[PDB]
Length: 50
Length: 22
Ligand SMILES: *[C@@H]1O[C@H](CO)[C@@H](O)[C@H](O)[C@H]1NC(C)=O
Ligand SMILES: *[C@@H]1O[C@H](CO)[C@@H](O)[C@H](O)[C@H]1NC(C)=O
Image (cartoon, rainbow over all chains, first blue to last red; front, top):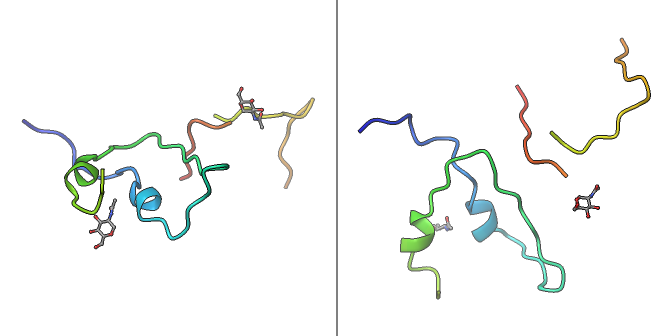
């Protein structure tokens, strides 16, 4: 099974590992488009409570 | 591919879903 190199990945690190977060009243809404979205880090990582 | 407002007659002098720059 062969596919192109897994590059041009979507920057989930700019969302989950952000230095500053918004309030719930007015949250930050980042558009994620035109990429490879790797969710294995978010799913398997033990840093998340849920 | 933004919802752009263009001039009545656009020229060059001398909501977005896609963006790319070379
Ligand atoms: C945030 O950075 C840490 C650095 O130790 C990394 O282990 C973690 O997976 C990163 N979180 C995300 C969502 O990439
Ligand atoms: C962007 O689209 C939404 C939904 O149609 C609209 O309510 C909003 O006013 C638009 N923003 C601009 C700058 O056109």
